[PDB]
Image (cartoon, rainbow, N blue to C red):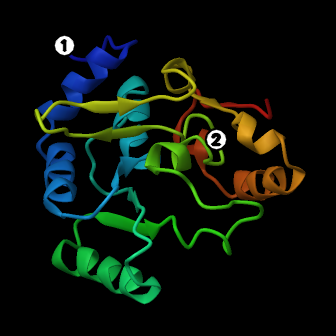
Amino acid sequence: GMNTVKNKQEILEAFRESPDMMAILTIIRDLGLKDSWLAAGSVRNFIWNLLSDKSPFDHETDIDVIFFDPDFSYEETLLLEKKLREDFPQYQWELKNQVYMHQHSPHTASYTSSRDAMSKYPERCTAVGLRLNEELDFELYVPYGLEDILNFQVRPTPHFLENEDRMELYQTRLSKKNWQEKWKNLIFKNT
């Protein structure tokens, strides 16, 4: 049955059909963090595997949970990360405050919001979001279009090619990624 997916609708139905993919969402909702949501590879995992006859629902891959809280302490960010993983070892909560993201990258001044931080990820297919809203829907964000994910493309954003130092961060962080190694139809690009 559920397999013949080429579009958002057919993917989003499968997300909610999974208890575990839902669970990870319902928890980050109640977390009371500001400006956070599930974005990048976490959300992508249930979408790429879906189209590759893999396990979209394994819950045993990394869980990108960015946020923006300039009022929350640098250290408390790392403290809260351990609390996520202690209380719930079964998931791989990656808690990263994007405020302090000036030191771990080249020319990356502070973002306006989580969606802006998204359009400034190392790849276009990475610049994507999924969470619930006030109606308990699927909020989606695809700043480059859905097709980058459906065709399994790995290209940099235009925000990267503008600055050679940002390209050097991408290229270095390409080779050690087991992309094509997990997915036998994963396209690589530089543009």
Compared with 140, 72 (above or below) is below
Label 2 sits on what residue type? Glu
* Pointer 1 local density, CA inside 10 Å: few below 14, some 14–19, many at least 20: few
Q: Is residue 84 left or right of residue 22?
A: right
Label 1 sits on what residue type? Gly
Q: Is residue 135 left or right of residue 11?
A: left
Provide the secondary structure element on which disc 1 rests: loop
Provide the secondary structure element on which disc 2 rests: loop
Image disc number at residue 39: none
User: Residue 79 location in percent, x, y?
Assistant: 34, 86
Instruction: Give the CA distance from mark 1 to mark 2.
Output: 32 Å
Q: Which quarter of the figure is the N terminus placed in? A: top left
* Pointer 2 local density, CA inside 10 Å: few below 14, some 14–19, many at least 20: many
Quickly name the residue at label 1: 1
Quickly name the residue at label 2: 123
User: Residue 58 location in percent, x, y?
Assistant: 27, 48
Name which residue lies at 34% across and 65% down. 92
User: Residue 165 location in percent, x, y?
Assistant: 85, 57
Q: Is residue 120 left or right of residue 107?
A: left
**Numbered disc in front, either 1 or 2:** 2
Locate residue 103: give its quadrant.
bottom right
- Looking at the image, which is closer to me, 120 or 2? 120
User: Residue 43 location in percent, x, y?
Assistant: 37, 42
Compared with 180, 30 (above or below) is below
Compared with 5, 159 (above or below) is below
User: Mark 1 or mark 2, which has the lower sequence index?
Assistant: 1
Name which residue lies at 69% across and 60% down. 108
Name which residue lies at 56% across and 73% down. 100
Q: Which quarter of the figure is the C terminus placed in? A: top right
Name which residue lies at 37% across and 78% down. 72
